[PDB]
Amino acid sequence: GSSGSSGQGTPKLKLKWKCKKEDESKGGYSKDVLLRLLQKYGEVLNLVLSSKKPGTAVVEFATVKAAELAVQNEVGLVDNPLKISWLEGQPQDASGPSSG
Image (cartoon, rainbow, N blue to C red; front, side):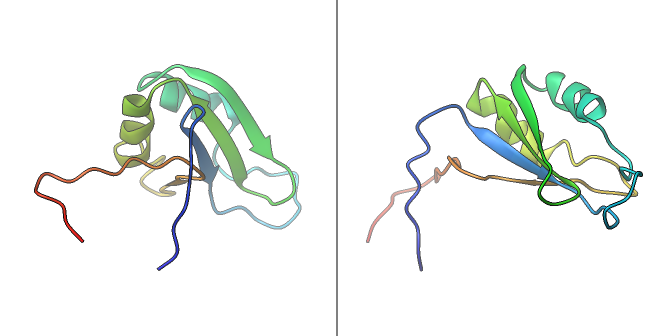
């Protein structure tokens, strides 16, 4: 298909969740909640939020291990399973002999 991501710097992740139109109500999360949710897994060096679109943000991890676990295990809330996607620098490894 189409691939080509350098991802050299820290493994930053993008946190997106379902949120209503421009409203005073967030939905069911907050810089803190999300911060503590990841903290447990890994130290959150920087945690920024996206204003352009509602229910969107980007977290900055210090290690790859934590990030992954924060993208697999931590899903947010049963009712609202946060959408943690790899904005850039995604881990890729197989448990067998690779080839063309």
